[PDB]
Image (tube, rainbow, N blue to C red; front, side):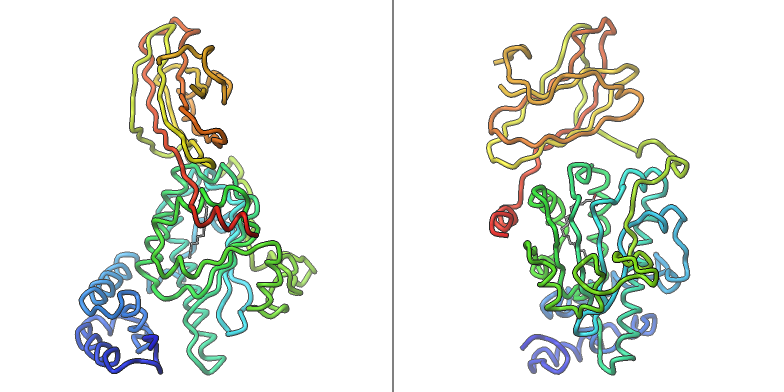
Amino acid sequence: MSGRVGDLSPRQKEALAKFRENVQDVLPALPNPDDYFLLRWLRARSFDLQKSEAMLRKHVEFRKQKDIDNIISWQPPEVIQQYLSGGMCGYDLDGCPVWYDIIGPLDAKGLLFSASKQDLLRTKMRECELLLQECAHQTTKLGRKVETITIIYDCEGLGLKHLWKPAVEAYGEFLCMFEENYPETLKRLFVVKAPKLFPVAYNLIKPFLSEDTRKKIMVLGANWKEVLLKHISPDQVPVEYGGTMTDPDGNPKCKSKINYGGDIPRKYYVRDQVKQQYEHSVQISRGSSHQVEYEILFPGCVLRWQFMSDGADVGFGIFLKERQRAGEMTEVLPNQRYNSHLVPEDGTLTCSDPGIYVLRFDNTYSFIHAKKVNFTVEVLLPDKASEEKMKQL
Ligand SMILES: CCCCCCCCCCCCCCCC(=O)O
């Protein structure tokens, strides 16, 4: 059996009936606690009554604290409405709403510098409620239950700038929220136009995804447009993605439904940086330097770092190798001075050649003494399975 309405084993039916009795006290506060609704929670925890109940009660508490009942009427900040990419557009062959995620032109720094992380997360919650509401409308129009969504995840333009830690963490917060509050809602997710950086980028959010979500992700190759047309009718897919749908004015991208992001104009900023902490701190003497070592053995790794200096700029460069002078080592990222005391510095480097990498903070050119440098560095690894897919497609 599949644990779905109309296909329950006697044990699952008994569990469903018991589950309803056990959570009776919170059902009135729910929009429509039918059997489909309850079974999403049971399936998400393999019909373990205790875990399923804990999951649903936590969701109920979440709805209360986030005022989900009124979130659709809540209007997100102007900068978010204008620049947060993505959009609901069309229905798949089964009648399920399709959601488009446009990663490339998303300006995470711009959004985080112009709005609170709370409003960003709330906007995402709202999109989820808008999608569920669309499912409810499709259920009425099609005369049958529609409760899942199809996602087209456009990774064209995915680059190193998207690995910026604060953005990834915020996104991770959304994903955990989605996994805990909208179980059994994702039907299928098509990753299209995934670039070379995909395996590393995916490995960053993979920890936030449930096994059920991971199994629904399909990384598509060169024939992605044809694959989409096997699940979605051509008139329901924008011209931009291989279909025939366009905006009334003839735009192939259907911008009336899909937001394509873009960099946020400086006039919207309310800050030039987000609050930041570092895992390490060193005091560098005048005319001296400090070396930080990381062994990179696996190819395809990416070094990601963030650092700030106190009161004065500092030099920074990355080398490949015991304490050697910069000149004795191989220069991978040319040493340069950064005003990391004015604006926090962050960066990434793709590590092609394995070896011992040395990030070197340089103060050899200065008399300013005891410069305090705060930094955080990580070696980002590629998701093995994803690496293999990139070789196939
Ligand atoms: C419903 C959401 C499912 C999640 C699907 C994730 C598919 C892989 C996404 C990799 C994204 C790369 C990281 C981008 C981080 C950012 O937003 O800046």
